[PDB]
Length: 450
Ligand SMILES: Cc1cc2nc3c(=O)[nH]c(=O)nc-3n(C[C@H](O)[C@H](O)[C@H](O)COP(=O)(O)OP(=O)(O)OC[C@H]3O[C@@H](n4cnc5c(N)ncnc54)[C@H](O)[C@@H]3O)c2cc1C
Ligand SMILES: O=C(O)c1nc2ccc(C(F)(F)F)cc2nc1NCc1ccc(Cl)cc1
Ligand SMILES: C[C@H](CO)OC[C@@H](C)OC[C@@H](C)O
Image (cartoon, rainbow, N blue to C red):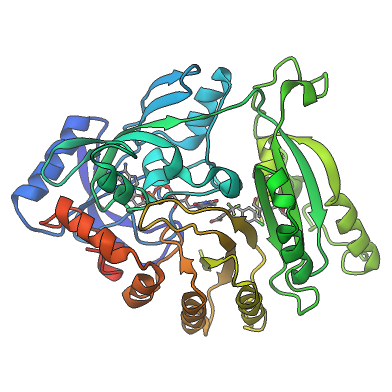
C-alpha cells in the first residue's frame, strides 16, 4: 500500500493533473481510503483508474485521490458449464482471454486493444467489432460488487433489486463507486479462430450500401477502415472485414490439433522487413488500386485474433493527436454523409479511421452506443483543430448522435448533456448513491456530472 502524488493523463497525453495515487493489492485498504474521503466530507473525492487506455480525463482527479485498480487482478474462477467467470475488476481482457481459452470460452466483447481492465470495460460500457450482434460489455455482466460512498459493498445484478444502480454503473465512468469484482457470462467457442470475408468499396456510397443491403446479419463481427482524406468520389471508400468464430472442422488439418491455441506476437513486423515504407511507383495508380481491391477481397479466410481483430499490429512503429469518436442514428444517412464531407474538406487529415454499424442499444442511461453509424478519426493537433471539433460536436448533436467519454477530453457539459438525454435520470441515481460527492474526476467536473 503506497500513496503517491502522481501526474496523470489519459492515453491522449493531455490535460494533466496531480492526484494521490493509491496502489494496493489489498481490497480492505481500498475500502478504508474511500471510508476516509467520506469521513472528511467533503474534499476533492476519489476515482478508480484501470490501465489508463481512455484518451481523456475520466480516470484522473486533480488534487484528489486516484485508486489504481490493476493490482486487484485475481481470476477467482472460470466455469465452462455455466460459462461464467468471477474476476477482480483489475483483471485485463488479454489476461482473461488467455485464462479462458482452454475452457472453450471467449471474451464476449473485445475492444481494439486487449489492455483494458474489467473495471474500465464496464465503466465505459465498451463495444467492439461484434456490437451489432452482441451489444456492449455491460450486456454480459451478470453481477458486480460495487464499493459505494457509504463504505458498503453492494452486490448488483442487471435484473435484481439494485438494477437501477447496476445500469447506472455500466457506462458510469466510475462515478457510482469502485467496481471491486464482477461475474461475466462468456461466449462459448470451439476455436481461437475466425472465418473472414473481406470487401473493398470504391466510395462512401458503396460503403453505406454494403452495410445496408442486409449482409450484416450474416456476420457476428464487422468493422471497416475508411478513407477520410481523399475528395469524393474516393472519400469514404473502405476496406471491410467481416466474420464469425470458426468451428473446429472449418480449420485446416494443420490447426485442428490445437484449435483453442493463441499465437505469439512475432519479433519481426513489417517496419522491420520494409524500413523505407511500402510505397512503390504503382501504389497510387490504377495497378495500385487494382492490387488493393484484390488483397482486400476474399471469402472464408481463416484468421487468428491478431489477423482478424488487430490488423494495426503488423504496421508496428507506424502524442500530437486528437481522437474523435461519434455515432449517428441509423436513419440519419444523409446527415452522416454530410458529416464525413465536412471532415474531408476541413483541412484536417486523418489516416486511422474506423467505420462500424452499431446494433441495438442497452438500458444504461449513459451508454455510448446507439444503433447507427459509428466513426473514429485521429487528427494531428494543429492550428484550427479545437474550434473545428467544436463545430463537429454541433453537427453530431443536431444529427441525434453523441460522443464517447472514453475518447473525450474537450467537449462542453452543455453539448454532452444534450447528446445524452437520459443524463438527468443518471445524475439522480448518482446523487442518491453519492450525496457527498465522494467519487469525482476531472471529467465529472468538466462535464458537470459531479
Ligand atoms: C488503441 C485503443 C483502442 C480502443 N478500442 C476501443 C473499442 O474498440 N471500443 C471501445 O469501446 N473502446 C475502445 N478503447 C477505449 C477503451 O476500451 C476504454 O477507454 C476503456 O475504458 C479503457 O479501460 P481501462 O482499464 O484502461 O480504464 P481507464 O481508462 O483507466 O478508466 C476508464 C474509466 O473507467 C473507470 N474505471 C476503471 N476501473 C474501474 C473500477 N474498477 N471501478 C469503477 N470504475 C472504473 C475510470 O474511473 C474511468 O472513468 C480503445 C482505446 C485504445 C487506447
Ligand atoms: O484506437 C482506438 O481508440 C480504436 N477505437 C475503436 C472504436 C471502435 C471500434 C469498432 F468499431 F471496431 F468496434 C474499433 C476501434 N479501434 C481502435 N483502435 C484500433 C484500430 C484498428 C484499425 C484502425 Cl484502421 C484504426 C484503429
Ligand atoms: C478499423 C477496423 C477495426 O479493426 O478494421 C480494420 C480493417 C477492416 O482494415 C485493415 C486496416 C489495417 O487497413
